[PDB]
Amino acid sequence: WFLATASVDQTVKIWDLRQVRGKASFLYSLPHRHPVNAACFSPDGARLLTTDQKSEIRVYSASQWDCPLGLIPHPHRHFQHLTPIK
DNA sequence: ATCAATATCCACCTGCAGATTCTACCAAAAGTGTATTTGGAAACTGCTCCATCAAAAGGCATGTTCAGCTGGTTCAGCTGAACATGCCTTTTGATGGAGCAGTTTCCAAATACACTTTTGGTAGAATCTGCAGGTGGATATTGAT
Image 1 (cartoon, rainbow, N blue to C red):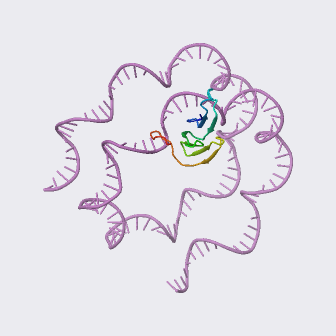
Image 2: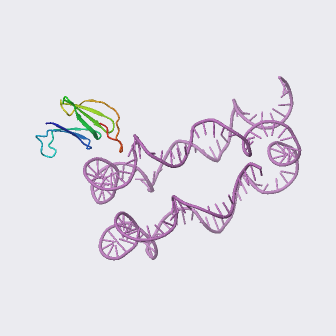
Image 3: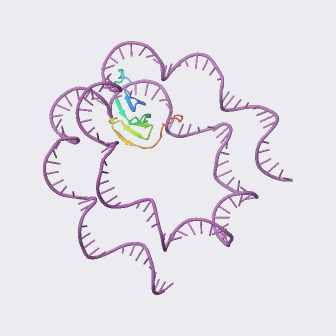
């Protein structure tokens, strides 16, 4: 009963699907400098991976979603006819 | 190598045309204050830039062949720099006096500025045709012979 979603708005949002109903009465919001191509949870559940379109990877933790633990810089640049990277 | 001839740089050095100093003004720089005008930080919309992967068309890196150009040599003219000489167009240096550069007066001719009223020049949606492209064949052009 917590959810993750990613968007071209340069933000990635963590929801609580049972509690929220109010059109962005969300739980947490993490910003970025560029768009996001993927936001995938762990198997254990405590580590969120996030992957942008220009050059970055971020790891956010269970503990205080806002601040990141670590950045893994690596270029996976976006392109029209290319399949986006995950 | 050397030594005579001409041209060139360098120490002494002086009176003055050009450089600098100095008065006395007033036509430009700032202050104060105000009225007017802007460039750049938030929203939003619609072209069109980032530069992968198959499939295919056509251009180039390589190698091969040889004729005709480069660029070196030798040389018969020829022509243009040096120069003396005279003399004669210009250099300084004055003097006149006519008239254009330039200034001032002022107002008749030409224009901004602010408003209202036409209007045609410009997107966008329906029609056209000259030329891209194709097809094909006669004559002009290179070149072997």
